[PDB]
Image (cartoon, rainbow over all chains, first blue to last red; front, side, top):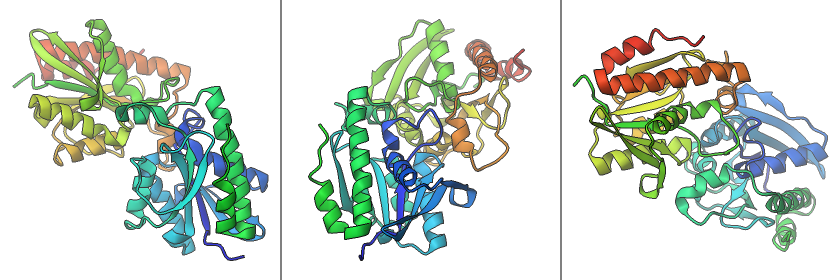
Length: 196
Length: 196
């Protein structure tokens, strides 16, 4: 089946202290996808991150979790995409999404960064090309804008984390469906899911 | 001239709240100076951070810990410095310094960002001006470029943290000395210090 995605990126800050923070939600998806496919990601300094190649339905999907600062995610994504000759429209970036609630996830093509430091850098390093795909993992949002960075760098409370974990798992399933049945069918499934 | 400083900024990421990570070293200095001087740091959304005002030897010293993403620290700094008409040469930015070991600290004017995302943004948002002062709190350098973000976003081991905390204490004393006796004398004390 024809489907557009050659590279799946999961945005993150590195290390143990950031691993369970909301702003690492996209990495959670890639980690669970790789685990289910029995591939351990390898550190590749030239790509500023951890990478692997998955065989799913049995398309080849490269995956990446940058080990840069979140605000330098684009260095990883560009370095890898250039090496493998991948264009922005063939990249899906999974990330935490303030404008969706915990337990929801959506696919989208294009859009702004929404103030997400990793998406901002990604757009920049891909030559101001916004037309990469996104896997938007809802995290909710705080009451006040000035509290957004503290929010995304916090750990969700247990109940909220259950919703997020559910949406991660269903996003993984829909990525597997993307590789079997294509984007429209994957999206139709994902966009009816709501954990609660 | 000998006491140029009107604003002391302590860089840090604003979460997770559970975690004393190396890249928050500068905020530790501002928090301890504030504690000793009975200043409560208060959220001030128009400056994108926690703020205070001290009076030490009749010199007003405003303090800021940005609550932006680290790579937007200069947005907070410039917001406050513009509001109070403080020039860049009147600002001292306390920050983790890869180029000194744990237990050592130094004052300097100008210099590059050395890869520090907060310093980089600060130079930019101050109108591409490096000539603010720095309080460099040594955190050591991991010996390879690849995992620098992971290193600064890590928690120092308990022993190393004792060295850090000792450098924070000495840095607070030398900030007090700067406000009383001026920068040359404050340097003469700080630069001969090593934690024991």
